[PDB]
Length: 196
Ligand SMILES: [Cl-]
Ligand code: NA
Image (cartoon, rainbow, N blue to C red; front, side, top):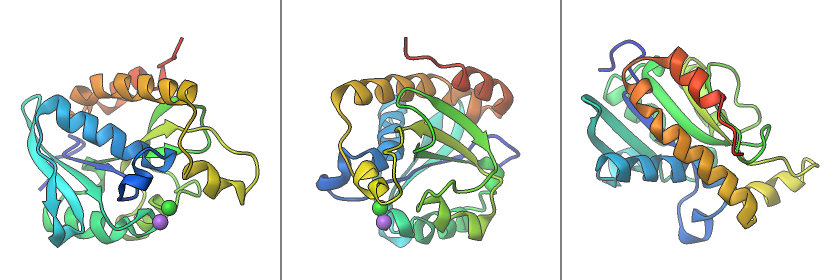
């Protein structure tokens, strides 16, 4: 199983398929694929958990990575059975996701709280509760509530993509603190990020 608030499962939320790969709603996928490449964690086909997953060493800690392949609004049909099978408590889980409530280039580490209207988190919190950690990757808001779909399934303009990419790069450099259980310090150092 997991051990205390040493992060040992890192989830990236998004949609499968080339047509969704570059959309804001895949910010979580961008973070976990970049983290997998940084630490040489293989992301392989995991049909038993309806996802793509990996396991490897991050800074001396055994860590699993998961990209649900369920579509966003069914993410819990991967995350929940995965976390149960491996006996990973929510307190040892980080979920990286796009955050409509924050600007491109803003990134925050949050413990607990609601789904904030996120259709991926909304499929997860009912089953494992809220007490997992979140890497909230700012994607901006579109204005109106029907305009939301068009925004999260949009490919960001290059300036917004640069801002998100810089924030994601910053968060990659702080994963060492997270897998070491230094959540307070990782929160201080991630939340302080400025693009410029
Ligand atoms: Cl979606
Ligand atoms: Na969906």
